[PDB]
Amino acid sequence: STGSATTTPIDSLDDAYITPVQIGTPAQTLNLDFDTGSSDLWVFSSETTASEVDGQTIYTPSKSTTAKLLSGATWSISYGDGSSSSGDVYTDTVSVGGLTVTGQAVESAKKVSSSFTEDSTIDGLLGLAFSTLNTVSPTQQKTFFDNAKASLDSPVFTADLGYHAPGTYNFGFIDTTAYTGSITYTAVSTKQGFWEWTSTGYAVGSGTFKSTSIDGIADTGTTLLYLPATVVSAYWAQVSGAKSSSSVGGYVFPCSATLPSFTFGVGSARIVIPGDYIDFGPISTGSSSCFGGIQSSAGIGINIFGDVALKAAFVVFNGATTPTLGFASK
Ligand SMILES: NCc1ccc(C(F)(F)F)cc1
Image 1 (cartoon, protein in one colour):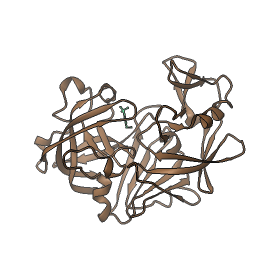
Image 2 (cartoon, helix red, strand yellow):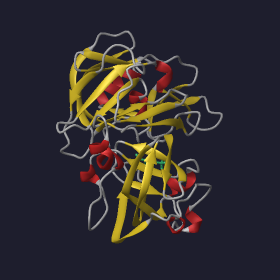
Image 3 (tube, helix red, strand yellow):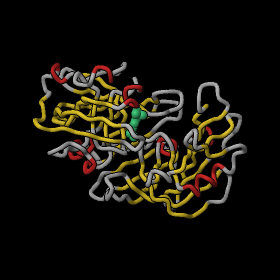
Image 4 (cartoon, helix red, strand yellow):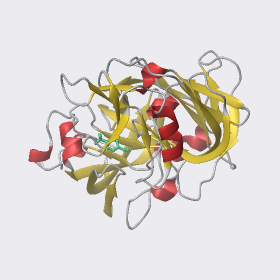
């Protein structure tokens, strides 16, 4: 079997991408943020604290004839940005673009942090990292992909994120019309539960390629590209007026600048991120200081190939016995 669903940026900056997901019987459609950086499928629900819901679509397990309370199960998760959520668990039928998983753990939120309440467009998250990161206690639960894997035509999912445009999440098949050239596959370490891999280096604009190993995660749930301070300083040194600002919390640059591209290595292959992808607009409404899409990973403790990098490529998350990542230009 296969699945195919369109993913759409939540706003004009591509801060995040939402993908419609059907939960329960009759179907309840919620727009979830597909996140390869986490492994919990959680949703705003009829159990979420009323003052913490502001425009989100909720899942009401009492209206689903297939919903079952997963007795005694709770979940609690904290994300890299400081956001968090927690609640109880139901099992229910969940489908993504035609692909159905019966008995999928649907973590119903009882509490959500302010960042989630403020994002009226995001009804929850659908984790796609390894199930080892799943927070359901006392019985750890599998991701949607892990549960669908055996039934898929090929044990893969692909991320084809658009730049200020819709894109596609495919499950179980590789669309050979969605990319140019060939897909370059690279090794993955699952030791930290992420799609963790090693980039072979970088270039800034038309500069010479620097061969250097950059360990990092392919994370659809992270907006920006977080790389080592050396790499990020080399990039921003090419933009007149660019600087790191502690008051803003990162590199900012004059909104009047035309940014250089950023190339990242995938084995002997190169993925070019166009300069316009690196512009995250004014730091505040009406400001002439723009926020950079390439930031330092120094405070995080891991490099993150977020949406800025992933949207420049057709990306294969190969969940075979030996998992790999494939990258192709598009
Ligand atoms: N990396 C996961 C993630 C995704 C979205 C959000 C936000 F911004 F919607 F709250 C936080 C954390």
